[PDB]
Image 1: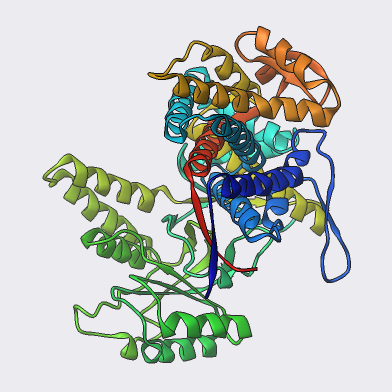
Image 2 (image 1 turned 135 degrees about the vertical axis):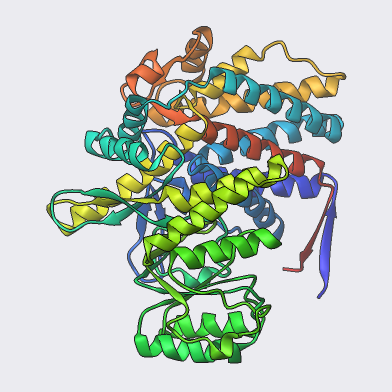
Length: 524
């Protein structure tokens, strides 16, 4: 109903207070010497967390304006985490630093748009310098070392990741699965991974990983929009009689249909997950047919004439395991005759040599690569169940980190990369003095995370920051052992994607914060 609006300095200082509270919450959990923070729970047992992702998830301020600012910073930090797999705390610290210094400059009389342009210029130059500084990791030894470093210096997980990428491919689909016994066997199975996540966060049955897991599910794929329940009633009853979960992949499931399947999943009569089918246009239909071939099913397309009412359980395909993340899905070991899979691969290749342009042939190459590459499952195992669980968590984290590293590269971790590129960009200039002020703001913010890490360590921030500043290359400071040296050799690695994404998203949110002049929020 009625809303109150704040114009000028008041709204911006409300954002400053909100982001400062979020930083107070999160930045203390940065670096190896990360202080514990208590997240109270209504059930009765408070949870102590050293990771800032949960802390950011649990922050929500009381004042509407401060809450709005903190929530925008949290949103961009979550975007950075989704894109890179890490860097939530670093992105939040960078964003808070840029916001603080930019607001201090604006209150002096600087033009917010010029400050944003200076921030953008400095961040672009920093990304370029980071790409220059990134150390490639494409060899098997480099991949193994990165995987080992990420998962608390364990050689077994590093070897598993290295051999998995050797088998399925450098950019192949790799997933972690609980394995039976002490040994951890690895093999490749037919499957796909199209990056279009769940329609609703109410399908999540594994909230710890923030993902959706189905065991031996049924794959129902229809080349049509679904917004009515009566079409899915027969297939839902059929799968409920079967008892196995059902996976829905179609153009879109919205309206009463999405609500009713969400309600049914929440009640627990039958577990159903729905994700919209990959692509759009004719390529969407081609990918849907490829999935049906992979999982030994048929496409329920209204174009042919047959519809969901007559859809039996036999015509729709099935798989052995489906993992649906926030952004992607993974059919693992789809049951289906390999003869049909090779026939589809041959047909796609024939289309490739019968292409008309480079774009369509590239799309066909992507499709055939996803279809024929397969999925490598890491059946990680340990002596006990809890050890297997915690080892699986470590292996999944290492897999994410190694995927990021192989995608972009490895650069000096612990905030050394950001301060190094800030040093290398000491000569940046803008077309105006305000742009220079913005560039200086960006550089100071870029050096801030190392200062916060060494402050949580205990040592004086300025001295360590200056000492790292004087050095060249990847030489930096390790808070774990309070000694200097070459960072990558000593084993403190952060993927180039993580730092790049953190810096870029912090710059984006800071630019949005600085230039904001009004707020429209509900009355308290």
